[PDB]
């Protein structure tokens, strides 16, 4: 109710600047663009506009997406093709990144800090990682997993987040390697389709398509309040930005917005969509800066390192064996 | 229910074979790609040519499986990606006596039994195992719909005959109340 | 015929799943490793606990799928070489009123519903897609035979039970008059 | 005549004008007037072990005129029937209160064959989808083919050019590889429905095979796949067994839906049915000396008969758990002909496959050929 920080007086942060109101915290840089998948296309929309921008076209079944704001990339999954691809955000140079091994690649997230691509496959019942080029590929979690959908990264915090909508309905987090596998919420869930981190707010939001709620919880999952509890016939994907929440809804076939704290100002940013899928806010502050755990240094032991805790741990591909925390070998 | 149906070679019905009920399953939407087909039906006819049953998207080369009477015999043809095959019943079907048809397809291999004959079996050419389909299913043939370039000639003759007891897989079909595109509620006149 | 014949409970019968009786087909005989199942098996019970049907074959780590009454709820399980998966229904099975069941596994992915409950679907751990059958599952229960070791305390029951209307694959089992290894002759002393 | 037939050979008719001689219509010869010899040559019947000439009953290369100066015994050891029995492989000495097991605890061992002068047995398991090898010993089993099979119906060993062929009635192909399974090339693919039995002719660089698909058919090709041709598509439904009499310059085959065991020249002409009874469901056929041997899924037995008379019909082993492919284990059952490749520059680059009267160079899956001698991935 003070946007980002108080102590009577309000405060902004990082690349934000208090609006002519001194509660509101506007983001610096370019205008936020809402980026999202459409089964057939990948599109761009401007939160309070009719606006309409076809970014990628001849696509079979495009579900999950994410990006690398710097490096100017865009990855996306395809559930019939069972592939994960990337492109020049330009919209050019499209290329196969995860070919064999996919069934229902639901979740897809990019770790812009450590240049890693993470995804989930609810057919495979497993979460996986890789280089941006699509190489150095390695499975990450396979234990207990049923139907993982949404996946969120905190490169700064070196943590990963997700939702499991199988018979044990879960919102879990672990560290970017697979350690510290914790339950964030396992109660009053059934269809947790969406999940997003609001760094600048130090909170996580998620979406339940059975329970008709957008929920907010501290990153440890404590202080869990539902924010919106109506107008949610069937929500699928969500994203925060500034004070607003954006989500796709399969019933209303649309991109809806609303207020993070209140759940007031419910809006249909766009109606008449083919099939709204994954959505993100496309903006710099959505990919906030963070220290590379492998920086001016051993950029990945032999192959790829995984920000765990603080001390990044070393990591070997599928088929490979460790031999040390400097060394990888088949 | 409505228990038998009458086809004039100008009545073409759509049903919904195999879908993804995303609204209900919370599953990501897609084309069902099927390993398996099974269906039973009783048929009585006088025509010696005609398309009776059609599973698949109605599009160009798009996977399909169809049953047509051709030259007084029944036959099953399906195509999965690799070239199709045809399974010709050793049976004469123009006898105006009700006949029970059985068709089943596990991956590449298919079979067909007309009455109490010995099942004519076969394999579709190596390379394709999934019947890739929106889940459309059409009874009696199709209207201005014989899709792409593919088919043998008689697959454009409308049925002209009668059907009942239609099973699609493990589900017994509700003829009238399951129709998704319906001409007219017409029960079958037994001679 | 016997379109309804039921059970003693002291009756424990390995019905005949499937064969390729070459003798007719002239195909080469083989125990087919499966990936396609299904049925529509009704049920009545009072026992909040017990076992029902196990498919496949018996030996130490000999592939299986199985159904059992766990805590009153009903879970279907199976293992393919990679660890076993469990699919539990959300239905108290105690009724003594009559309940219908459906379950299907297409390769890795399983499915099971009791009544009109939304289909509980699941997945087998990756790297094992084969189920290994004789083509004669067991049913009701047995004596001193629960193999290997993967059994919660519901898979213990020599479940004295009464059911009806069993189906295997797509084809209906004529209950007892062509029962496989018939133990007793009698319908249910029904509620 | 009747005074002048006092000595007019055979058939006298003092008709015509005054004495004219003839013969009973088989002795036809007429030299000079009053005399009448004999007519043979051969062609029509005359089935003595080998054959007649101008009167001859001489055993062929590898046989000895036995004490009845008709039938032959094959030179070498006494031959054995080796047959696949599904849960194992066994061999039997025909006509004996004996039969030895060989390899044990198999899954579904269907089709087999052997490299004699290499102490090798090959067999295909249809339920493991493999084609294995083991030392004739019965030892060190090595999977020779391990992917790509569905129904390995038949095995074929070119003992002369050391190549192994087989038929998958699940993929509808015929594929050839090295004796170790290396250099795997899919040989024939088109218009193949349900190909079962396969039989070779290394001497002539020639294959033979059954297909009980929708167009049932006995076909033939030159080792290399070129030179395909129909042997028979007339009167077949279940052509199960096929086997060559290499000595007899003939081919005998078995249809289990017609219940026959027909026989023909290596082009298929002059096809007489040979056995038309006691054939409920025969599966695999084999010849040796003067005898036909087959397996039958109904009786569950090894059978046998005279390859000419068809009489002499016989039960060998009864009670086999499920007899599949059968074979005579004997050196003369694998005659050493000329090696069409010779020194192994003939060995080509990868595969030297006999073609027509010469041979060709062939490439395993993946490999395009460059300039007819050489293959490249
Ligand atoms: Ca396909
Ligand atoms: Ca396995």
Image (cartoon, coloured by chain):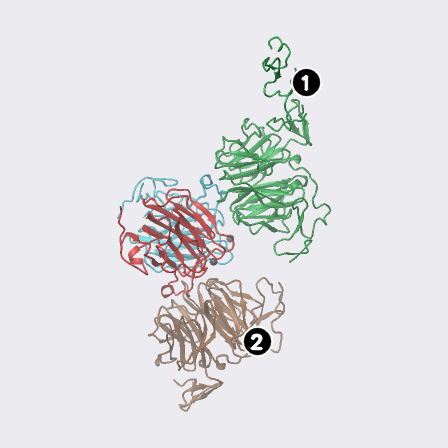
Chain colours: A brown, B red, C cyan, D green
Residue C27 is labelled as none
Residue A158 visible to the viewer: no
Q: Is residue B177 left or right of residue C127?
A: left
Image coordinates of residue A188 in percent, x first then y, are 37, 69
Q: Badge 2: few (under 14), some or many (20 or more) residues near its Cα, within 10 Å?
A: many
Against A208, residue C129 (above or below) is: above
Label 2 sits on residue: A293
Residue B105 in picture, x, y percent from top left:
43, 51
Of the residues tagged 2 and 1, which is closer to the observer? 1
Residue drawn at the location 53% of the way across and 42% of the way down: D217
Q: Chain of mark 2?
A: A
Under circle 1, the secondary element is loop
> Are the numbered discs 2 and 1 placed on the same chain, yes or no?
no
Image quarter of the C terminus of chain A: bottom right
| Residue at mark 1 | D32
Across and down, in percent, residue B114 comes to: 38, 45
User: Could you say which quadrant of the image residue D221 lies in?
Assistant: top right
Circle 1 packing at 10 Å, graded few (<14), some (14-19), many (20+), is few
Q: Secondary structure at mark 2?
A: loop
Decide: is B180 above or below B105.
below
């Amino acid at each position: 109710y003070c946007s980002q920080g108080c102590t009577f007086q309000c405060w902004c942060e990082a690349g934000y600047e208090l609006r002519p109101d001194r509660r509101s915290c506007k983001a610096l840089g370019p205008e936020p663009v809402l980026l999202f998948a459409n089964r057939i296309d990948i599109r761009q929309v401007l939160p309070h506009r009719s606006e309409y921008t076809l970014l990628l076209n001849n696509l079979e079944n495009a579900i999950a997406l994410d990006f690398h704001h710097r490096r100017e990339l865009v990855f996306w999954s395809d559930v019939t093709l069972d592939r994960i691809l990337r492109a020049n955000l330009n919209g050019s140079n499209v290329e196969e990144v995860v070919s064999t091994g996919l069934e229902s690649p639901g979740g897809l997230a990019v770790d812009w800090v450590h240049d890693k691509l993470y995804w989930t496959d609810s057919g495979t019942s497993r979460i996986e990682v890789a280089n941006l080029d699509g190489a150095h590929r390695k499975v990450l979690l396979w234990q207990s997993l049923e139907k993982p959908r949404a996946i969120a990264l905190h490169p700064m915090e070196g943590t990963i987040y997700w939702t499991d909508w199988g018979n044990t309905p879960r919102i879990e987090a672990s560290s970017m390697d697979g350690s510290g596998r914790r339950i964030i919420a396992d109660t009053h869930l059934f269809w947790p389709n969406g999940l997003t981190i609001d760094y600048a707010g130090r909170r996580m939001y998620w979406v339940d398509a059975k329970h008709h709620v957008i929920e907010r919880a501290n990153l440890d999952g404590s202080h869990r309040k539902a924010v919106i509890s109506q107008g949610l016939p069937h929500p699928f994907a969500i994203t925060v930005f500034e004070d607003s929440l954006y989500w796709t809804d399969w019933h209303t076939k649309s991109i809806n917005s609303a207020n993070k704290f209140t759940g007031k100002n419910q809006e249909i940013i766009r109606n008449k969509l083919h099939f709204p899928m994954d959505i993100h806010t496309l903006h710099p502050q959505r990919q906030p800066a963070g220290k590379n755990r492998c920086g001016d240094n051993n950029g990945g032991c032999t192959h790829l390192c995984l920000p765990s805790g603080q001390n990044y741990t070393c990591a070997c591909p599928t088929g490979f064996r460790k031999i040390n925390s400097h060394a990888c070998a088949q | 229910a409505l228990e038998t149906l009458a086809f004039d070679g100008r009545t073409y019905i759509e049903y919904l074979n195999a879908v993804i009920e995303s609204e209900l399953t919370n599953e990501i939407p897609a084309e069902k790609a099927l390993q398996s087909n099974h269906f039973e039906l009783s048929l009585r006819t006088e025509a010696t040519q005609g398309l009776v049953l059609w599973i698949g998207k109605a599009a160009e080369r798009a996977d399909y499986m169809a049953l047509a009477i051709v030259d007084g015999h029944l036959q099953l043809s399906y195509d999965l990606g690799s070239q199709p095959v045809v399974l010709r019943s050793t049976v004469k079907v123009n006898t105006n006596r009700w006949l029970r048809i059985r068709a089943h397809r596990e991956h590449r291999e298919g079979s067909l039994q007309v009455g109490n004959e010995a099942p004519v079996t076969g394999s579709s050419p190596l390379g394709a195992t999934q019947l890739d389909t929106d889940g459309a299913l059409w009874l009696g043939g199709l209207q201005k719909l014989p899709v792409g370039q593919a088919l043998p000639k008689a697959y454009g003759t409308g049925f002209v005959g009668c059907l009942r007891d239609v099973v699609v897989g493990h589900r017994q079909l509700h003829l009238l109340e399951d129709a998704v595109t319906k001409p007219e509620l017409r029960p079958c006149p037994t001679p």
